[PDB]
Image: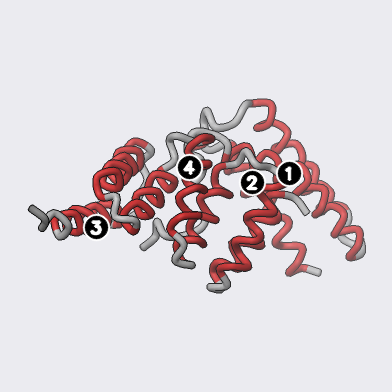
Amino acid sequence: PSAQELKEQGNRLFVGRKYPEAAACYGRAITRNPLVAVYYTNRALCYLKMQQHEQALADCRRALELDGQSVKAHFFLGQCQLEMESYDEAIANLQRAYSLAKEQRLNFGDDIPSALRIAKKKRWNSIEER
Amino acid sequence: DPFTEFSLESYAFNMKATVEDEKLQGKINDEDKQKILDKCNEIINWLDKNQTAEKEEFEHQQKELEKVCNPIITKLYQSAGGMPPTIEEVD
């Protein structure tokens, strides 16, 4: 089976909400061709749904080594940072995601500004310390 | 069979329109851009003549066409995009 064929099987599994099984497909796809960034971002998303902030972070990192202009790598990375309470980085990555999508003329509705607005609020709820 | 035959022919025509799209400019070299056009035009042509052929014969043409396209597909991902709650979906 090819790397592309394996990604597609994994995507079908993702839509079916069978996340662990979908991640296994992405890994196998990575094995046959480890130099395609999407396979890393997809699997990061499986990890995010499986509530594993740490492993998803690593796949984002790999994705950005290959594709530094990736909106979803920057986006999911911010989201991992938000769930690990690294607020300042997360807002950076989300805003960097936000700049890229504008340049590339991508259209995700109001998805990025929402995420940005939530993170800015979460941050303030943390600064309650003096 | 017309229903299976339809997916192959439509795949072929659409794939051609895709690689020639102004959006994918600078995401594919004209050499790879040209070999998709070729194999699509070849598969379409085959369907035009072989309307008596059998399932295995159809299947062979199908496997062949995706053996050229998938690699080029994979390189589209490897460009500067790569190739993308809507944002919360696999690509």
Q: Depth check: give the residue in front, A63 or A72.
A: A63
User: Circle 2 marks a residue in which chain?
Assistant: B
Q: Residue at x 64, y 26 (%)?
A: B30
Cα–Cα span, label 4 and label 3: 23 Å
Cα–Cα span, label 4 and label 2: 32 Å
Q: Position of residue A129 (x, y in %)?
A: 11, 55
Identify residue for label 3. A114
Q: Secondary structure at mark 4?
A: helix
User: Circle 4 marks a residue in which chain?
Assistant: A
> Circle 1: is it few (<14), some (14-19), or many (20+) Cα within 10 Å?
many
Q: Secondary structure at mark 1?
A: helix
Q: Is residue B10 visible?
A: no
Q: Residue at x 76, y 42 (%)?
A: B68
* Discs 3/2, front: 3
Looking at the image, residue B19 lies above or below residue B84: above
Identify residue for label 1. B40
Q: Depth check: give the residue in front, A108 or A64.
A: A64
On residue A61, which mark appears?
4
> Which residue type does callout 4 highlight?
Arg
Judge from the rendering whether residue A14 lies leftward or rightward of residue B58; answer left or right. Answer: left
Q: Are marks 2 and 1 in contact (CB under 8 Å)?
A: yes
Cα–Cα span, label 3 and label 2: 35 Å
> Which residue type does callout 1 highlight?
Cys
Q: Are marks 4 and 1 in contact (CB under 8 Å)?
A: no
Identify residue for label 2. B15
Q: Are marks 4 and 3 in contact (CB under 8 Å)?
A: no
Cα–Cα span, label 1 and label 3: 42 Å
